[PDB]
Image (cartoon, coloured by chain):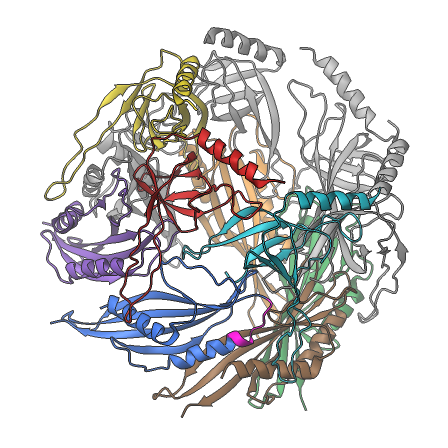
Chain colours: B cyan, C red, D yellow, G purple, H blue, J brown, K orange, L green
Amino acid sequence: MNYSQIERMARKGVAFFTDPSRPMNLIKQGEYGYDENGFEIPPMEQVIPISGATRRPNAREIDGETIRASDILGIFNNDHEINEGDYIEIDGIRHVVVDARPVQASLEPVAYRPVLRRVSV
Amino acid sequence: MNYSQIERMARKGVAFFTDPSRPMNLIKQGEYGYDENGFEIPPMEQVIPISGATRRPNAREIDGETIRASDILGIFNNDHEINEGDYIEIDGIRHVVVDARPVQASLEPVAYRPVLRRVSV
Amino acid sequence: MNYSQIERMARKGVAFFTDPSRPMNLIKQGEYGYDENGFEIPPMEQVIPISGATRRPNAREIDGETIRASDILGIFNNDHEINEGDYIEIDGIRHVVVDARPVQASLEPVAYRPVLRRVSV
Amino acid sequence: MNYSQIERMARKGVAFFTDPSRPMNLIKQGEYGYDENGFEIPPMEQVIPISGATRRPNAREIDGETIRASDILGIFNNDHEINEGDYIEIDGIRHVVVDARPVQASLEPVAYRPVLRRVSV
Amino acid sequence: MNYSQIERMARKGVAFFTDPSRPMNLIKQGEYGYDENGFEIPPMEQVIPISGATRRPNAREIDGETIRASDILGIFNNDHEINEGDYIEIDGIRHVVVDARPVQASLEPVAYRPVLRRVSV
Amino acid sequence: MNYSQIERMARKGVAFFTDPSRPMNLIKQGEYGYDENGFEIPPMEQVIPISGATRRPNAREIDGETIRASDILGIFNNDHEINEGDYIEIDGIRHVVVDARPVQASLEPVAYRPVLRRVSV
Amino acid sequence: MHYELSAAARAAFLSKYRDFPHYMENRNFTPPKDGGMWLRFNYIEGDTLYLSIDRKCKSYIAIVQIGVVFPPGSGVDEARLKAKEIADFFKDGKMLNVGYIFEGAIVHQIVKHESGWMIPVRFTVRVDTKET
Amino acid sequence: MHYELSAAARAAFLSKYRDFPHYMENRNFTPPKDGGMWLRFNYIEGDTLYLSIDRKCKSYIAIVQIGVVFPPGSGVDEARLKAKEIADFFKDGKMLNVGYIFEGAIVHQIVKHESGWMIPVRFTVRVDTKET
Amino acid sequence: MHYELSAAARAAFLSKYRDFPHYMENRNFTPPKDGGMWLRFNYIEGDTLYLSIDRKCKSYIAIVQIGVVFPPGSGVDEARLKAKEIADFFKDGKMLNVGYIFEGAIVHQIVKHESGWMIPVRFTVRVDTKET
Amino acid sequence: MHYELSAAARAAFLSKYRDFPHYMENRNFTPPKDGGMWLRFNYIEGDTLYLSIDRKCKSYIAIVQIGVVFPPGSGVDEARLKAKEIADFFKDGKMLNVGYIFEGAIVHQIVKHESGWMIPVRFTVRVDTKET
Amino acid sequence: MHYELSAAARAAFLSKYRDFPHYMENRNFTPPKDGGMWLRFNYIEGDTLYLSIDRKCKSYIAIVQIGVVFPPGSGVDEARLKAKEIADFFKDGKMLNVGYIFEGAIVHQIVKHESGWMIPVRFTVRVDTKET
Amino acid sequence: MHYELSAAARAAFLSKYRDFPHYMENRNFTPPKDGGMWLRFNYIEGDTLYLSIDRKCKSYIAIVQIGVVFPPGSGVDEARLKAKEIADFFKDGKMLNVGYIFEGAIVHQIVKHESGWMIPVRFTVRVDTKET
């Protein structure tokens, strides 16, 4: 079976349920390393734009301390591959990609369905 | 896809299953801050009217002490955006919006589906 | 949408699956209050007749002590509103209304679906 | 709605999925009472025949001690009303009626669906 | 209703989804008994052939110790009745019949659906 | 019923949802044994190629330590039979076959549906 | 001598509360339809102590628990009055016809449930036997 | 003498806080619609001590817990002020009309919930009875 | 010497209760169809004590538990009578053919279930071995 | 004197960290959008000790916990530096305006989560009151 | 000296039971098809004790557990005989080629399962090392 | 002085095992594709002790845990050899550049999982500070 046709269908479907006014960025900080004593920071941010769709909002409850946090799920495109420790800048709010969950039956996955949790607590 | 049409459909649907005789208000108390020793109260109430629909009543059981509390779920409109710590005045009874849960695939959500729990216990 | 038509439909539906030979009463004891030392009883019974339908019988198991108790669920009408601490006299057996659960999307609910547990243990 | 027609339908349905060769009895031991010191036994057995259908066999596992017990569910008729502490003699094996579970929306239930567990362990 | 027709249908259905090349035996060891001091073994094996179908393989995980065990479920015929403590010799591997689970609504069950777990651990 | 036709259908179905560019290998290390004191390693690798399909990615969460592991499920062919302790080399990443789960109703299973977890942690 | 101890406790309990609704161990009993309070009877085995060095003179300890259950939303006044009467009847040192009360008239905290509450009243009995 | 002790505690509590919204054991009570704070009353049974060797002079211990519940997102200032007033009213050594306070004015840690918090205030009462 | 101890306990138990329905470890057994009571036999390993300094003379401790199970709704009288007979048979100090009873005739509290109850009777056995 | 103690602790904390993002008890607060670290403030009630025999001179103990939360995948260096600064500021023996620090500058082990970590810094305060 | 201790224990175990079916740590092993019994081998680390004041002469403690698993419904006689043989082989004070047995021949209670039982046999080994 | 202690421990660990694959706290790290073993580094805070009466001279205790994880079905020989090397490197009394090792070279029992095992090696460090 042809996977290019599936890629085109997935791209058009993602472009259907999307709004071209939500600012979404992506952070790929990496290449860390410790000093000869243990003092160093990763000097990479690598902010790039991205667009997609979101669904299923959910609220965070920890101890009844009224922290008022939330987390959602998203659907994205194949370019700018997502990893297991990246950050997503959704409407000025950072989320961490806990799960990548590519929609994959072949190499070079057609799309990604990451699971995002709000950063900090 | 057009989201204005979805907004109109959601507004008409909410206006369908609603009763224009239930008094419903909304409280947006905010802008707190402590004194130079720690004595101050938030001087804001911001009571505004609102209308919507409710569903799925549920009862509260804690210890068998016969407190007789209850909590429900609601569906509302896009104006007067709901937050994660607001109060809803349903028929003279206060409820706290634990979860916002907007029905969102785009900015400026078309509607909200908050989860309400009765205030106090 | 019109709620009077829904009320008529619910009333006829309740009157369909009902048997006009099961004695059912309702108790609204209330207006208590303690003495100047703490000795007083609520002098109210307020027994009124009622009719409805029941479903889903269930058995009570606590410790294996063979107490042989049971509890059911019911569907009732809009008049003689049910509360969270009332008693139901089903066939000479008392049950306590743990949950009211009105079928409500508007004021003056069309019907009630209480959850009853047998009194004592 | 008429319940006599439902009774006839239930009786014919029970008589359909039944085998008129399985010996089934019923025990209604009762009217106990203690002596002036506490020594007395209930002098009642009240063995009566009965017929019905059974379904959903299940096995009992306690500690890995290989006791090899089993329990089932049954469907019966309206006559010889079942109670919460009766015994059923299915193919020479005693079972205790833990749950009565009448199929009831009216007085004089049309049929019973008891839950049986094997006696002893 | 006639149960002989159901028996024929079940037999043909079992004979459909079966492979007449899998060696399957059955063990009915029994009639044990202790000596005057407590030393004796059951001198019965009673190995008889049998055929049937299997489904739903499952793996056993205990402590992470890599024991690599497995267990399955089976469907069999009415002859050579299965009990709650018999052994099944599936492809040279022993399994213990934890649950008999006859497909029964009458005496002399038409078929059995035992649950098998691999012997030892 | 004929199982060769089912084998052909399963083979074609597996060959449909597959990509002939993902490098997949298989390891059958075995025939271990300890020395006269307890020092010896298994001198077998037995790397052979294989192809198939994968589905349902999943992420591993242990303590919040950001290990970023993942595991998937797969569908394979009948040749090169899978066992309960083999390794799968999917895109240069090793996975351990915790469960074999053959799709079996007969000897020589038509296909396998193993459950793979990433090696190490 | 452990069966006769339970027999004596039962004999005393029925001697005092024959007519009140009550529950007994391993007997089918249904709560009153009127929702009123009923009594609960339980027997808890203790331990047997070997007192001497020849393992002849022994002792038996047992615990008897009586609980009162009352409907929710009906106060805790009459239940406490009934518990007080129960405690007063089973005075310490009372001599049964097989043994005697080692420790009596103890009232513990209330256990709460959404269908019915319970106030447990508990005491202990003891008997001494010499084996010859 | 355990029913009269609870009666005395209730009498004192209503003598001080008759008008404030409050909850009482095994009575149907609904929280205020305005979301304001309400009081909570509980009675915890203790143990009865046999002091002498003739098992005549006894003693009764009990625990009374009063909790204040306040809506979330409304601070912890006024709740602590109310708890301070509660503790000051129930001073140690206060003589009730049936007994006296053995140990009073104790404030414990706050328990948190997503619907309402609670600050528990707890103290104990004691009575001595001689049986003749 | 731990296999012979269990053998001796089994020998005594069958010497007394050969005909009564009973269950034995790791043997397929089905409860009586009539719903009557049956016996239960279990062997619980203890610990082995090294008594001397040359690690030669040892000791073995074991626990034997016998339980009686009776149908629900049939009282607790005959079960207690059977437990009393069980306790009387296994008197303290009884000399088995491999060892002797270290501690016997103990009856514990009843465990309840919705299908069948149980009264556990428990005792211990001991043997002493000298290694040469 | 327990409300003023919390007031004094809050006064000191805002005197040092007015501008840093922080959370306060029972107040709606949202974490920073930039994902940076924020402070956490909690007040844990202790116990009140009756020191003398006339039940007049008392003592109050309380526990104040400050936690730092930092995003995952960002190291543990700056968090430990901030914790060190927190510990250094709240030196032992520091005299508050209502009480004093009984025990200060304690750092406990890190608690891990898949959304954000936390390093808890904890100390205690004490006040002495004489009742006349 | 902790790797050589496990090596010595393995060497002894294979010296005695080379041919019997057995399982070894972190090695793929399948139970016998015939359903017969097989051996189980595990190594449990203990603690290392610093004996002197210069932190030079040390000690190592370890626990070795051998379990026998036998099919359900096949009695407990031959399993106990095998456990007795296991205990007799690993006599106390036996001198290994790297260490010696600190405590041997202990048999614990049987663990039950619906697929297979197990009788665990456990002992300990010790070694002493002087660091120079 | 608690940040510098962790810094010193990290400095030593990288001084010995710079090239071996390893994991560090709160840093994104993926296990090797080849399935080989990798090191694990954790820092566990202890407690700070106030030694004198003027609350000036203090002490800091910390726990450092290093774990080795190895694939299932690959034996436990090389893992134990690596653990032995780890223990030998971190000898007791070793002087770090900020502190010293209070207690070193401890190996605990193996934790098992169906995806990967782990042998934890644990030791402690201490530092003394005088405040002026």
On the image, the x and y values in percent for residue C113 come to: 47, 41
Q: Is residue J44 above or below residue B27?
A: below
Q: Is residue H76 magenta?
A: yes
On the image, the x and y values in percent for residue L79 come to: 69, 52
Q: Does any portion of residue B86 appear in the rendered image?
A: no
Q: Is residue H120 above or below residue L68?
A: below
The one nearer the camera, H119 or B55, is B55
Q: Is residue B12 magenta?
A: no
Q: Residue at x 34, y 17 (%)?
A: D51
Q: Is residue J77 above or below residue D20?
A: below
Q: Quadrant of residue L6?
A: bottom right
The one nearer the camera, D32 or C13, is C13
Span of residues in magenta: H73-79
Q: Does any portion of residue D15 appear in the rendered image?
A: yes
The one nearer the camera, L71 or K83, is L71
Q: Quadrant of residue J39?
A: bottom right
On the rendered structure, is B22 left or right of G68? right
Q: Quadrant of the N terminus of chain H?
A: bottom left
On the image, the x and y values in percent for residue C107 come to: 54, 48
Q: Residue at x 19, y 28 (%)?
A: D44
The one nearer the camera, L65 or D103, is D103
Q: How many numbered marks have been drawn onto this rendered protein structure?
A: 0
Q: Quadrant of the C terminus of chain H?
A: bottom left
On the image, the x and y values in percent for residue H107 come to: 45, 75
